[PDB]
Image (cartoon, rainbow, N blue to C red; front, side, top):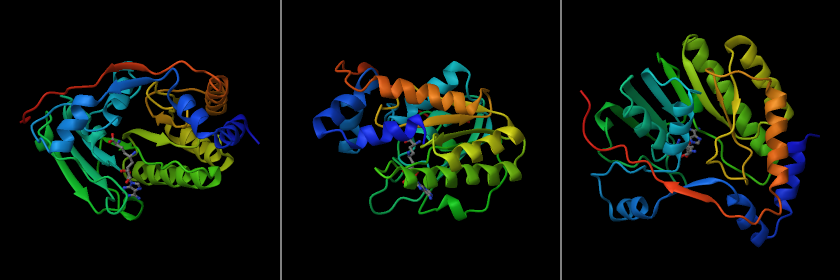
Length: 260
Ligand SMILES: Nc1ncnc2c1ncn2[C@@H]1O[C@H](C[C@@H](N)CC[C@H](N)C(=O)O)[C@@H](O)[C@H]1O
């Protein structure tokens, strides 16, 4: 058993009050009041982020932890926060975004955010059974939280296997992907194997809630995986009892318009 397993048990033992206070303490949170109401009324001309994912991927790029370039695929795009971010980047030529959609899952939000015409959105697509194709950058933000850490470990394992399939099609492709439960043993095992063939490492974004152990793997960084995970687990364990609030920051506005 790991420190992350202990963090999970403590999280599940939280009352609802303890949960709401713990999940947001000390984290960066974009101010989404304007954006949420524009999306609610169905405004298509907007560059404000369609989701909290946009600022997360922007942080990774601004830090230099991901390379977004060429033909990008967004595996599990949801509303499309990562797709619209990538499409706004001048080094990106195209985005093929895929998400399952359907009951209980987010379909792409359709807006004119800068570069939207370079995105081909495909809803109704299960990426775990989709054949890979050529790509320069492979993104995947999949990993649904569960109180059951074994389920989360299995969901994480499926993502890594997906990235291995995309790397076998594209061995030189840049990769960034969510690792929902990085402390589980089958997850550490699969990340070690990926790192040995492809390089890379794990990083925590400051927008992630304390209620999730999610870390992001990218081929553009390095770092001992077990040490990365353990450092994060301790950071999470230390914020139990923290009553401070989130740090609120402005939401990303990418602008609107086509790119040609
Ligand atoms: N097997 C699957 N095939 C396709 N999409 C999936 C699958 N499993 C989960 N998803 C979707 O993957 C998405 C994961 C989200 N976290 C992505 C958020 C996105 N990066 C954003 O910035 O808005 C959800 O919308 C899920 O519905």
